[PDB]
Length: 272
DNA sequence: GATCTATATGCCATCGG
DNA sequence: GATCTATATGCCATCGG
DNA sequence: GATCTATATGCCATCGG
Ligand SMILES: [Ca+2]
Ligand SMILES: [Ca+2]
Ligand SMILES: [Ca+2]
Ligand SMILES: [Ca+2]
Ligand SMILES: [K+]
Ligand SMILES: [K+]
Ligand SMILES: [K+]
Ligand code: NA
Ligand code: NA
Ligand code: NA
Image 1 (cartoon, protein in one colour):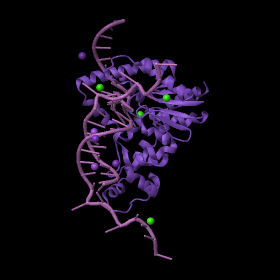
Image 2 (cartoon, rainbow, N blue to C red):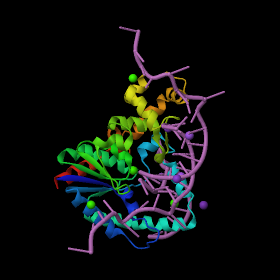
Image 3 (cartoon, rainbow, N blue to C red):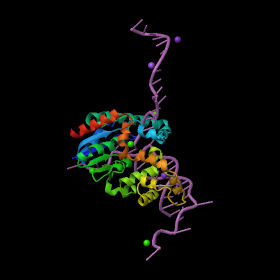
Image 4 (cartoon, helix red, strand yellow):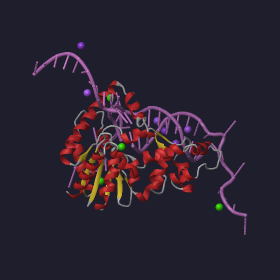
């Protein structure tokens, strides 16, 4: 039997329809129930977002500032629609709590809770299914951990990493995100390096820690000059994007007692 | 040329009497 | 009782994939 | 969130005594 971990705020956008004024709490819960059955999940854990990541803010005060800018620019009509949506989503979460173990921890990204759950209890299940449209959750893929995106309708598996992310494995994926940064979170990368040049450098030199150890790289191309100046950026970005390595620290950033209680609660759920 | 940077979509109810 | 005086918090990253 | 629009790189001598 399997474990299913839901990126719950992320999933809620499947219910955002400007031409529907109706509540969706019931359909939200039902969708999760049907996904759990589809994926033979004996355990389902629903995660939700609750404020910006304290762990990441500490390293980067402009973290997700781009998201604030996006919402700031809304028209009066858009704001009204969004407020209705987000109130309906809050109601969907409340209903969810009565049915599934559902976690929100202020100042902790759902990404980090998911990474930690997989590390703590993933071994107790045949397969782990991650319900998220967020490609960064593919930092967690293994032969036993896969992802489903409602947006693309695709299942993401470790063996298809190159098709999906232009890298061959998770370690290269994490390195690539550190070099490239993450536009969605307002984390700048090395200017001039995208997936193609990033993959080439990784293939040649290894992971980001290996690359740092070899700087300066040769070449007078601007993007290499930029890479050569980016040791501190790369170390920082690695902390921000290497979900499996830093998930425990990210949770502990809002209190060690909180981490200890979450650990306890997750272990207990896996026995229920 | 590919590749990268940067922007804007009021996105989104998979799929089966 | 309420009301006022006086003090101490190493406060504080709203909120949305 | 993915996806799309739009921009800027003075790019570029693969690889083997
Ligand atoms: Ca997230
Ligand atoms: Ca189906
Ligand atoms: Ca607001
Ligand atoms: Ca050849
Ligand atoms: K970049
Ligand atoms: K007074
Ligand atoms: K087009
Ligand atoms: Na560009
Ligand atoms: Na006081
Ligand atoms: Na666009």
